[PDB]
Image (cartoon, rainbow, N blue to C red; front, side):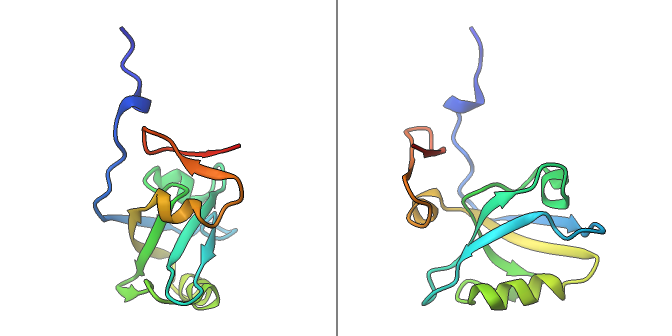
Amino acid sequence: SPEFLGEEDIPREPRRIVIHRGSTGLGFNIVGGEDGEGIFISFILAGGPADLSGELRKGDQILSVNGVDLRNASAEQAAIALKNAGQTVTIIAQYKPEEYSRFEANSRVDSSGRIVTD
Protein backbone atom coordinates (compact mmCIF):
# COMPACT_ATOMS: atom_id res chain seq x y z
CA SER A 1 0.00 0.00 0.00
CA PRO A 2 1.73 3.20 -1.18
CA GLU A 3 1.63 6.12 1.27
CA PHE A 4 1.12 9.16 -0.96
CA LEU A 5 1.83 12.60 0.48
CA GLY A 6 -1.12 13.68 -1.64
CA GLU A 7 -3.45 12.21 0.99
CA GLU A 8 -1.56 14.21 3.63
CA ASP A 9 -2.55 17.72 4.73
CA ILE A 10 -0.21 20.63 3.99
CA PRO A 11 0.56 22.45 7.25
CA ARG A 12 -1.48 25.65 7.63
CA GLU A 13 0.41 27.18 10.57
CA PRO A 14 2.99 29.90 9.88
CA ARG A 15 6.56 28.80 9.24
CA ARG A 16 9.94 30.50 9.22
CA ILE A 17 12.00 30.03 6.06
CA VAL A 18 15.52 31.29 5.38
CA ILE A 19 16.47 31.92 1.75
CA HIS A 20 19.98 32.57 0.53
CA ARG A 21 20.05 35.00 -2.38
CA GLY A 22 21.66 33.77 -5.56
CA SER A 23 23.39 35.70 -8.30
CA THR A 24 19.96 35.85 -9.98
CA GLY A 25 17.44 36.71 -7.26
CA LEU A 26 15.32 34.74 -4.80
CA GLY A 27 13.63 32.62 -7.46
CA PHE A 28 9.94 33.23 -6.96
CA ASN A 29 7.13 35.48 -8.16
CA ILE A 30 4.41 37.18 -6.12
CA VAL A 31 0.84 38.27 -6.74
CA GLY A 32 -1.70 40.22 -4.69
CA GLY A 33 -1.01 43.38 -2.72
CA GLU A 34 -4.19 45.29 -3.57
CA ASP A 35 -6.20 46.68 -0.64
CA GLY A 36 -4.54 44.48 1.99
CA GLU A 37 -5.53 41.25 0.25
CA GLY A 38 -2.02 39.95 0.92
CA ILE A 39 1.14 38.92 -0.92
CA PHE A 40 1.18 35.36 -2.27
CA ILE A 41 3.77 33.19 -3.98
CA SER A 42 2.51 32.35 -7.48
CA PHE A 43 5.60 30.65 -8.88
CA ILE A 44 8.79 29.05 -7.62
CA LEU A 45 11.66 28.80 -10.07
CA ALA A 46 13.18 25.34 -10.42
CA GLY A 47 16.71 25.39 -9.02
CA GLY A 48 16.40 28.91 -7.63
CA PRO A 49 16.99 29.97 -4.00
CA ALA A 50 13.34 29.52 -2.89
CA ASP A 51 13.31 26.07 -4.50
CA LEU A 52 16.64 25.11 -2.93
CA SER A 53 15.16 25.93 0.52
CA GLY A 54 12.51 23.30 -0.16
CA GLU A 55 10.17 25.02 2.31
CA LEU A 56 8.06 27.39 0.18
CA ARG A 57 5.24 26.72 -2.25
CA LYS A 58 2.76 28.35 -4.57
CA GLY A 59 -0.12 29.52 -2.41
CA ASP A 60 2.00 30.62 0.54
CA GLN A 61 1.25 34.13 1.78
CA ILE A 62 4.35 36.11 2.74
CA LEU A 63 3.56 37.55 6.17
CA SER A 64 6.95 39.17 6.78
CA VAL A 65 10.42 39.65 5.30
CA ASN A 66 13.23 40.09 7.85
CA GLY A 67 10.65 40.98 10.49
CA VAL A 68 8.90 43.62 8.38
CA ASP A 69 5.16 42.96 8.26
CA LEU A 70 4.02 42.56 4.64
CA ARG A 71 0.47 41.36 5.22
CA ASN A 72 -1.00 44.62 3.90
CA ALA A 73 1.83 45.72 1.60
CA SER A 74 1.46 46.39 -2.12
CA ALA A 75 3.32 44.14 -4.57
CA GLU A 76 5.71 46.98 -5.35
CA GLN A 77 6.36 47.36 -1.63
CA ALA A 78 6.97 43.64 -1.28
CA ALA A 79 9.34 43.61 -4.24
CA ILE A 80 11.31 46.47 -2.68
CA ALA A 81 11.51 44.75 0.70
CA LEU A 82 12.66 41.53 -0.90
CA LYS A 83 15.25 43.28 -3.08
CA ASN A 84 16.60 45.15 -0.07
CA ALA A 85 16.58 42.14 2.26
CA GLY A 86 20.28 41.34 1.82
CA GLN A 87 21.95 37.99 1.23
CA THR A 88 20.08 36.11 3.94
CA VAL A 89 16.32 36.54 3.68
CA THR A 90 14.06 35.43 6.52
CA ILE A 91 10.47 34.89 5.48
CA ILE A 92 7.47 34.04 7.59
CA ALA A 93 5.03 32.24 5.30
CA GLN A 94 1.61 30.67 5.67
CA TYR A 95 -0.16 28.34 3.25
CA LYS A 96 -3.47 29.88 2.15
CA PRO A 97 -4.49 28.09 -1.05
CA GLU A 98 -8.14 29.15 -1.03
CA GLU A 99 -7.16 32.81 -0.86
CA TYR A 100 -4.44 32.24 -3.43
CA SER A 101 -6.72 30.47 -5.89
CA ARG A 102 -8.82 33.62 -6.15
CA PHE A 103 -5.95 35.24 -8.06
CA GLU A 104 -5.07 32.54 -10.56
CA ALA A 105 -7.50 31.99 -13.42
CA ASN A 106 -9.22 28.60 -13.57
CA SER A 107 -7.61 27.45 -10.32
CA ARG A 108 -9.17 25.77 -7.31
CA VAL A 109 -8.24 23.76 -4.24
CA ASP A 110 -8.84 20.01 -4.13
CA SER A 111 -9.92 17.85 -1.19
CA SER A 112 -6.25 17.32 -0.33
CA GLY A 113 -5.64 21.06 -0.09
CA ARG A 114 -3.57 21.16 -3.28
CA ILE A 115 -3.93 23.93 -5.86
CA VAL A 116 -5.19 22.66 -9.20
CA THR A 117 -5.52 24.57 -12.46
CA ASP A 118 -7.91 23.40 -15.17
